[PDB]
Image (cartoon, rainbow over all chains, first blue to last red; front, top):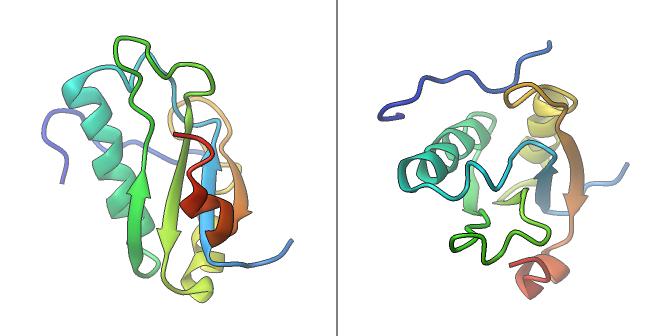
Amino acid sequence: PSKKRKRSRWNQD
Amino acid sequence: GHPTEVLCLMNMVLPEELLDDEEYEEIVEDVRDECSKYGLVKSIEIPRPVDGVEVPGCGKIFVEFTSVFDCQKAMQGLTGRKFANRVVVTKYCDPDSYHRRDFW
């Protein structure tokens, strides 16, 4: 999973 | 509103991101692992404007699902969310036009 950028998708609920 | 088979997700990407090698591939990965968290996903198609070759409309990704069940539960959590700092609009897409690739 990923390679450079961190996982920060879907942020509201 | 009505389940079909394919799930479309827009207003969550930008050409300024789908123009780099690692950047564009980055979203493809996260989007794949995300859609494949509620069930199974046949495949995914993401625009890739060549130095701005397909910018016109760019910023709309779609995912080919396998079961409408996991599809329903899919958007039921990633709808109106925020891929980064903007709301994501999810609209059930039909396998018809989908395969037609009216976008890219």
